[PDB]
Image: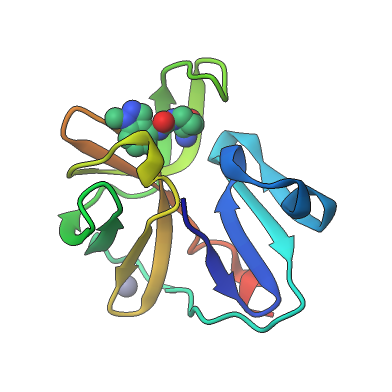
Length: 139
Ligand SMILES: Cn1ncc2c(NC(=O)N3CCC[C@H](C(N)=O)C3)cccc21
Ligand SMILES: [Zn+2]
C-alpha cells in the first residue's frame, strides 16, 4: 500500500484505489496501473522533473529503503493477475530489488523528488510506475 500526496491530488495504484478514490476521480489509466483522485487537504510531496535512473525506494515487506538503478519508462509485458488480464503496461521502469505484491504503492525518490510508485515485481525484480511526465500534478 501507499500513495503520493501532491497539491490537491492523491496518486495511487489503480488496482488498490478505494471507493472514495473512484468517487473523487481526476484521471485513471489501466495501461499504467495509475489513478489520481482529488483531496481537500494540501499534500506533503514534490514530484521530480528529471531523467534520473538511480534512486531509493521504500520496501514495506522489509521495512527498509533500498538504492536502485532502474530502466527508462517503457512498455513492458506483465503477466495476468487477479486485477488485470495479460497485457503491456506502459511508463514502467524495472530494477533489481526485492518486492512482494503488498509492496505496491511504495515511493521511489531521487534527489529531485518523487519519481514513481511500486507497481510490479518478480524474482529479484521490482517495477515502478513513473509519474514524472504528469506535469499537471504541480498545478
Ligand atoms: C513478486 N510479485 N509478484 C507480483 C508482484 C507485484 N504486482 C502484483 O501483485 N500485481 C497484481 C496487481 C497488478 C500489478 C500490475 N501492475 O499489473 C501486478 C508487485 C510487487 C511484487 C510482485
Ligand atoms: Zn531526479
